[PDB]
Image (tube, rainbow, N blue to C red):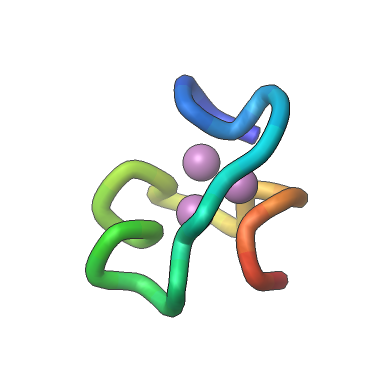
Length: 30
Ligand SMILES: [Cd+2]
Ligand SMILES: [Cd+2]
Ligand SMILES: [Cd+2]
């Protein structure tokens, strides 16, 4: 979980995820 992932993240696919998560943030839709 990066900055905005140490809890709950929406990240639908990448447009909002890959943007704030330059990695497989163990919490987005992965
Ligand atoms: Cd994400
Ligand atoms: Cd993240
Ligand atoms: Cd996440």
